[PDB]
Image (tube, helix red, strand yellow):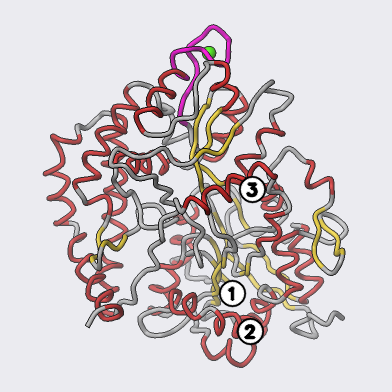
Amino acid sequence: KEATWVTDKPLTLKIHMHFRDKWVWDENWPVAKESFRLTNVKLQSVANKAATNSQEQFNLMMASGDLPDVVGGDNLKDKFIQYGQEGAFVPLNKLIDQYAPHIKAFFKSHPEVERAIKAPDGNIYFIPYVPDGVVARGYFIREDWLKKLNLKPPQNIDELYTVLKAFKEKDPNGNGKADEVPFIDRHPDEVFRLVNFWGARSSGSDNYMDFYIDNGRVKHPWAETAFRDGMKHVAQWYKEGLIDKEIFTRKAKAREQMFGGNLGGFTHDWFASTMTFNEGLAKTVPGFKLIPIAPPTNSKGQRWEEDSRQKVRPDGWAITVKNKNPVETIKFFDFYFSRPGRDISNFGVPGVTYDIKNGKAVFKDSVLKSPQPVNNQLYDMGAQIPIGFWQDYDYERQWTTPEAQAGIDMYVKGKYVMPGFEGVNMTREERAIYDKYWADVRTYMYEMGQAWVMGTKDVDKTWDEYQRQLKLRGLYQVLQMMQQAYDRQYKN
Ligand SMILES: [Ca+2]
């Protein structure tokens, strides 16, 4: 027996958790075993480990006719809310008040987070993944290449173009071939964020293609003329080969592949993990050195960092109506907002990945010296995964090098990080319009955007066509619903 046990008799719950198009909950995970040891609750995966489309698996599971006990994963907020209201998940409000003191206390001190996850009917249908941090992504460039070519870090978009063209044409890796790929990114969506360099927003938050507020008006970045003009530049950069030809398909291991193969020279990614490649590639890519740089001033005269750490992500887990043990389950969820639970969900397993020293979790030297980023190491063990848990930034601080820290501090002091969109509180009727049209609009936008970047469709020649589609697909009605919600909260 442990003080953290939520039940006297071992309880096994079925969980469908497929996330980030690559992982599934694994009961054999070191962290999964430790979770069971500490709570007396075991989670058995019913997900398809071989599947590569997390959202697709959620959809299939919901129509299986055999719902599990718990459902978890990334980017499921909208589905937890919609399906919760439709009767697939139980509301957690009262369960929390009565049996989840840590979560209750957390929501009391973070009322904004609680309001953000609530459905129009006022119910909480899932416990979210709460990030801890301030900044998210930043710009990184190859300083070793700048030195070889006698170039200075680019201070504005004109200089950035010049530098990237030099990386492309001056053989900085020295193999006598034009194989360098200036800009690379493990997140395809970052290619669109490049429009920031021409004064156009690409998203209102850390969630790609998100809405934003401009002087009290709800807008979608991809619907504005500034985006049209910015995309013409991005398309030109792709045509000139300054952008990875495979930017839309490389994905996940783009850094390992492109930096490891000494081809990439510039990216927009997270400070902690991106800086790990300097030590990680020290042997395989002699001289490799990425440095963080302030966002080059855009064409309009402003330095922009559009990304920021979210107060709460659209990830987490919920209790299905078929779960016969809702009380034990909410207590289990509560464990992840308590210090003991935050320890394993953030650091792994004691005696394996960390040890308690001076009363706090400290990563072992083996973990800190590994060439693989600490978060990547933890994913494979069941830690830093998108379940409902309270992230602890000290886990990240421990593997954030002085160089990475100097970059973070530079961005904070420079005030480059743009305030993120926190969302609006729609009524049931308003959100119904959102559920009806948004997913469709978003997919269409992405498909048109990819065509524009790859040059298969002309931005100017198809802009009016694109606008007609946005209207008949309901984007403007969605914006209207959101404007009404915004006004109820901030105006009148
Ligand atoms: Ca070369």
**Residue 486 has which mark?**
none
Residue at the spot 74% in from the left edge and 24% down from the top edge: 283
| Residue toward you, 138 or 481 | 138
Instruction: Give the position of the C terminus as an image quadrant.
Output: bottom left
Q: Which residue is mark 3?
A: 405
Q: CA distance from mark 2 to mark 3?
A: 45 Å
Residue range in magenta is 167-183
Which of discs 1 and 3 lies nearer the camera? The answer is 3
Nearest to N terminus: mark 1 or mark 2: 1
Q: In whole angstroms, how far apart are the C-alphas of marks 1 and 3?
A: 42 Å
Q: Is residue 459 above or below residue 15?
A: above
Q: Mark 1 and mark 2: span between their CA atoms?
A: 8 Å
Residue of label 1: 69
Dot 1 and dot 2 residues touching (CB under 8 Å):
yes
What label does residue 325 carry, if any?
A: 2
Q: Is residue 175 magenta?
A: yes
Q: Earlier in the sequence, mark 2 or mark 3?
A: 2
Circle 2: element type: loop
Q: Are marks 1 and 3 in contact (CB under 8 Å)?
A: no
Ranked by sequence position, the earlier of labels 1 and 3 is: 1
- Residue flagged by tag 1: what amino acid is it? Asp
Q: Main secondary structure of the magenta part?
A: loop
Q: Quadrant of the N terminus?
A: bottom right
